[PDB]
Every structure is written in C-alpha cells, then in structure tokens.
Image 1 (cartoon, rainbow, N blue to C red):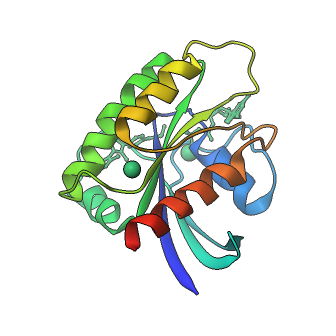
Image 2: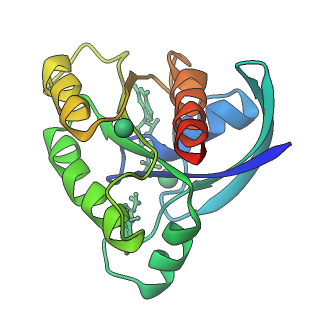
Length: 168
Ligand SMILES: *CCC(=O)Nc1ccc(-n2nc(C)c(-c3c(C)ccc4n[nH]cc34)c2C)cc1
Ligand SMILES: Nc1nc2c(ncn2[C@@H]2O[C@H](COP(=O)(O)OP(=O)(O)O)[C@@H](O)[C@H]2O)c(=O)[nH]1
Ligand SMILES: [Mg+2]
Ligand SMILES: [Mg+2]
C-alpha cells in the first residue's frame, strides 16, 4: 500500500480544517480553533488502488519558519485552498505556490487548486479566473463546500491522482 503525505494550505479562514475534518470524520465544524495544526491518517481507494493518506492541515502565523520549510519539503502533494467570497485568499494562492516551489527546488510539485465555500451565494472570485489560473499552473481545479461535502473527496482523490502521475 503506497503512503502519500498531503498538505492543505491556504489563507486564514478559507476552510482548511473544515475540509480535512469532512474527509476524515464526515462532519462539518463551524468553529474550528484556528491555531490547531494537526496530521490525520485515512486509508482510501482511488481508481481501484488503495493508498494511506497522511494529511497535514496547516495553521499558525503568516511568517517565515525554517521549521515550516521542513514539513513542506516532506509533503508530496498540496491543496491550494481559497474561498470563493474572499478575493484576497485567491490572490494569496500565487504566494503559496511560490513558497512550495522554493522549498522543493522544483516547478512541478503535485498541486490542486481548491475553490472552497461553493455553497455560498455571495461570490467574488469568478470560476473562469480560477479555471484560467489552474490552467496556467498546469494543475486541476476542484470546487468544494466543506459545509455540504460537495467536491470534498474529489479534491483529495484528485490530488492523489496528481501524485501518482508525478511519481511514474
Ligand atoms: C488562520 C490560520 C492559518 O490559516 N494560518 C496560516 C499559517 C501559515 C500559512 N502559510 N504562509 C506561508 C508563507 C506558508 C508556507 C508555505 C505554503 C510553504 C513553505 C513555507 N515556508 N515557510 C512558510 C511557508 C504557510 C503554510 C498560511 C496560513
Ligand atoms: N459556508 C461555508 N462555510 C465554510 C466552509 N468551510 C469552512 N467554512 C467556515 O469558514 C470558517 C473558517 O473555516 P476553517 O476550516 O476554520 O478555516 P481554516 O482557518 O482555513 O482552517 C469557519 O467558520 C467555517 O465554518 C464552506 O465550505 N462553506
Ligand atoms: Mg484551521
Ligand atoms: Mg501539471
């Protein structure tokens, strides 16, 4: 059984914890403590092949940390999470990708762009902007809602497909 280290990254309040808790414990958490940074394990079947996922839900301060570079270097795939009603979180995705690329001295790290809070009728980031950004990056884009569970397994299974493609 192949083991994969997944890292969930994105601005404060985009739903990093909510998506990770939906995937693992199948429930939506409205007030998850913003400081808690934890790892979760889950066995899943993706395209008829089982993998053990080890998912790091990131938290902490907006700061450079030579210790954060260490966790990031071990990550084999990343979810770049933005919220559709927060343009700043979508503008922030470029910075997050540049930091992942810097720490892994490469331009082809498995990544998935994730547009979270798709259940909200209030939208500031257009789907065409996110499709075009994922298009220039060469990565998939997955629309999700941690609240309704829409696209949640899809975002993580797609990241696994990306890691599997990269490792061949
Ligand atoms: C509201 C809590 C929360 O979401 N906090 C949080 C903390 C840190 C980050 N973040 N900013 C940067 C920059 C990085 C990062 C990345 C993505 C790769 C390599 C890195 N090396 N040092 C920092 C760093 C992270 C995780 C966002 C949000
Ligand atoms: N409506 C809605 N709210 C979400 C969704 N995901 C997270 N939230 C809410 O947005 C806030 C931030 O979520 P959280 O997982 O704590 O963000 P994190 O800081 O990126 O880990 C919380 O109050 C969640 O209830 C979603 O898909 N839809
Ligand atoms: Mg969190
Ligand atoms: Mg690619």
